[PDB]
Image (cartoon, rainbow, N blue to C red; front, top):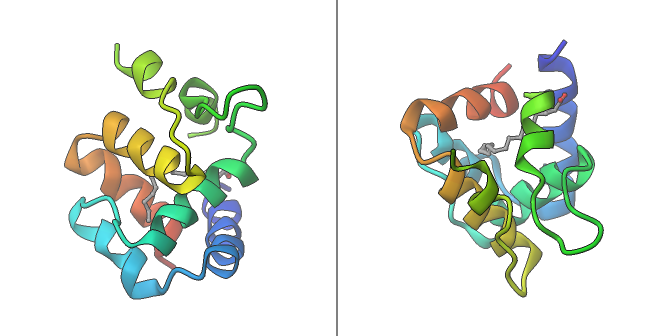
Length: 110
Ligand SMILES: CCCCCCCCCCCCCCCC(=O)O
C-alpha cells in the first residue's frame, strides 16, 4: 500500500540476515548500512522482490524502480559475495542522502 509490503519485507529480511534494528537504523541519516548482516539484509530485499538477475546476479535496478543516466553501470555490478553485490549497487546508485532516507523510512519505520 506500499508501507504494508515493505514492513513485511523488513521483518522477513531481518530474520534471514540476522541484522539488528540498530544496524539497519543507521539509514535514518542517509548512510547506507555497512554491517555484514545489514549488507545481507539488502540482498534479501532484492531477492524477495525478484530484482536479482538469474543469469549473472546483477541487480535489475530498472525493475526495482518500477516497484519503487547511472542505472546501467550500477545494475552491472557483480562481486563474489551476494551481500557485497547488493551493498555496492545501493552505494553506486543511491549516492544522494534523501534517496536513501526515503527507502529507509519505507522499510524501517511504523
Ligand atoms: C536499511 C534501508 C536501506 C536500504 C534500502 C535502499 C535500497 C533498496 C530498497 C528496497 C525497496 C523495497 C520496497 C519494495 C517492496 C514493494 O514493492 O512492495
